[PDB]
Amino acid sequence: HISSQQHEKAIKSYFDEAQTQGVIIIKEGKNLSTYGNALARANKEYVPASTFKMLNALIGLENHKATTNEIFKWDGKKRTYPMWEKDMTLGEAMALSADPVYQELARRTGLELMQKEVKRVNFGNTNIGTQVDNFWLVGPLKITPVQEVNFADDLAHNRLPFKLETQEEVKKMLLIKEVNGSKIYAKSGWGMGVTPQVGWLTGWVEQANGKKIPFSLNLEMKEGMSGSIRNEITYKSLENLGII
Ligand SMILES: *C(=O)[C@@H]([C@@H]1NC(C(=O)O)=C(S[C@@H]2CN[C@H](C(=O)N(C)C)C2)[C@@H]1C)[C@@H](C)O
């Protein structure tokens, strides 16, 4: 009974109140809905940053460069964040968004196979350039919020061109929240070495009844913003719309 004008206003205000510019795309069935305080971002290209980890893991697992219980050892070198200084599975690394593990996995895949697989699944502008272990951070790979939500929709419904088992193993890594019999699966992203900086949270909601509603939030991150503003705007938006 809440008007769409009111939903649009409330979700715009969540971005306004985080002092950022952003959009959140929701897809119900085949219909895309765009909300937020910067709608024109929906079809603009940004680096995928750590959202690329979902496809890196699909490619690595499909091509047997890793398994889901293999432990990627910390090599003992200092990492940007102390929580990355430990040994972890692809799964743990997904939740911590640990770039060093994903960089190692990309190097096992190698530049040639990586290029072929990123073209094969049709991700973003599909260009990875000549450096297998940084193309998702500063270019040249870019992707729009519409393309990210369509990727999430594909993964949520096992539609990507990988085995069903590869897709389920990656999906199991992405569970971030359970809210009233609803499950939220998502990957966050924060591209710090592009200007302006870009924040992402892309995934889907699995409702109690089995329906999956994919989303993609995309915003401008600014110095001394907390990463958790991405989750908060998302949960508020999905709750406002009655998806969770
Ligand atoms: C991916 O985009 C980069 C990493 N991704 C994230 C993220 O999406 O939050 C971070 S932030 C890093 C992870 N956990 C630490 C933390 O204190 N929290 C935000 C919970 C800091 C990285 C920048 C990746 C390419 O570096």
Image: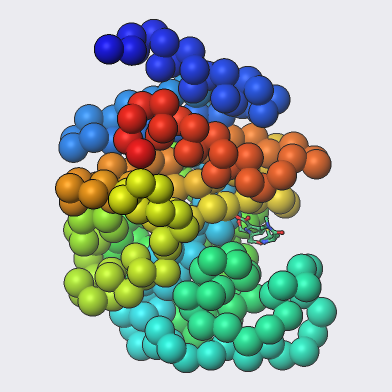
Q: Is residue 178 above or below residue 215?
A: below
Ligand 1 quadrant assignment: bottom right
Q: Is residue 129 above or below residue 201?
A: below
Task: Name the residue located 20 percent from the left edge and 72 percent from the top edge.
Answer: 164
Residue nearer the viewer, 82 or 61? 82
Residue 10 in percent (x, y) is at: 49, 17
Residue 54 in percent (x, y) is at: 43, 64
Task: Name the residue located 22 percent from the left edge and 30 percent from the top edge.
Answer: 31
Instruction: Say whether residue 74 is left or right of residue 170.
Output: right
Q: Is residue 84 above or below residue 201?
A: below
Image mark count: 0
Q: Quadrant of residue 22?
A: top right
Residue nearer the viewer, 33 or 48? 33
Q: Is residue 242 visible?
A: yes
Task: Name the residue located 67 percent from the left edge and 28 percent from the top edge.
Answer: 18
Q: Is residue 69 above or below residue 22?
A: below
Task: Name the residue located 35 percent from the left edge and 39 percent from the top edge.
Answer: 244
